[PDB]
Image (cartoon, rainbow over all chains, first blue to last red; front, side):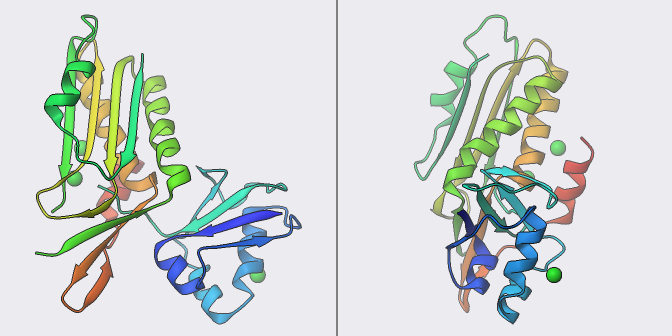
Length: 81
Length: 142
Ligand SMILES: [Cl-]
Ligand SMILES: [Cl-]
Ligand SMILES: [Cl-]
């Protein structure tokens, strides 16, 4: 499956830290759209133009392809030190 | 050529990190940057499986842009207070320009790509610290 992790505000709004989805999406974007479509909260969380994505712990374009076993993470712009 | 990457809650000491970073004679230029929390406690949320890797991806890119020697990057997590040291970047090179530029770059990319998020424990509740457009611009120049 693909494991999807959420952080910070995104996490708060989506209401879970992590979830699994089938590897039936060609790209991060396709997955983002599918997740956004689950509820108004998910759409709010996962429709921000500044949302960031990581695949296997690397930041990637939303056009990045997905593959079974990947870990995807969606999170807001970062604020570290 | 070695890189030290540490992400964790423990405090660090510039005097403890400096000797190692500066040890090689061929590393004639040593630059460090320490960033402190700027009264409310901050808590740094992070993506653990990614923070070290992201910091390492930034140093790898710096090494391709500049001829660097030892590099150390430390970023803390957990609850910190104004004045506390949150981040340390140590970079070495033969010449100052490379060392300064790589330090600046490493910081700029850390501030826009490393998955940490600060929350401030204010009187009315926790609040997420806002990302700064200035960090975006700084990062985009590289
Ligand atoms: Cl859609
Ligand atoms: Cl700064
Ligand atoms: Cl700078």
